Image (cartoon, rainbow, N blue to C red; front, side, top):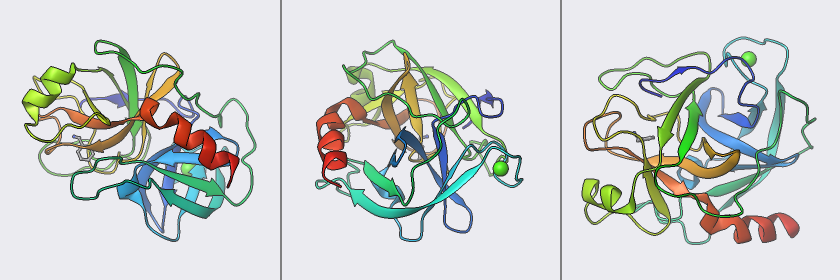
Length: 223
Ligand SMILES: NCc1ccccc1
Ligand SMILES: [Ca+2]
């Protein structure tokens, strides 16, 4: 997250870190045994780390649980990033508490102008590289479909939305991928892609979660 703020320990209780020897992507806990992330975060050997603040220090609220199963969206296209969503099942159910909690799925899509909370352990610099130890946060509005399409000609599908600031300075970044965009207490987006971080006229692009609620629910019901 570039241009954000320190969230505060365990204040984003649905935020998970995906670890394969190191943090490599975010995700969102949606029930005691399932995480939503980005399909482009897929790999084998995932340990889901819940209850994290500093990802380099054991601070006492962590739960580390291996994945038992990954399910990349049936229609994910890694070239266009259309349908950039995957589900991860935990080998055991997480213990839910005030610091480790699921986030509600949308009942309805969100509209441009809605404020949302974006979070992660990704790069905090738009030029160069500095990766934080503690969780970072950014409040950002959803942008209109027309603004998003103007910023990225030929690239925005019905499964994507832009959020952030056209002027630059505030955005998600590499290492935030897969993490949450929460609006009004609902998971509306997944950190997906863009062009660089926090550059003028290049806002972040997010997977539009409301389009996937039926698939998420029916996948969970049979897996
Ligand atoms: N600045 C948007 C973004 C997020 C994650 C990865 C690449 C780009
Ligand atoms: Ca920790």
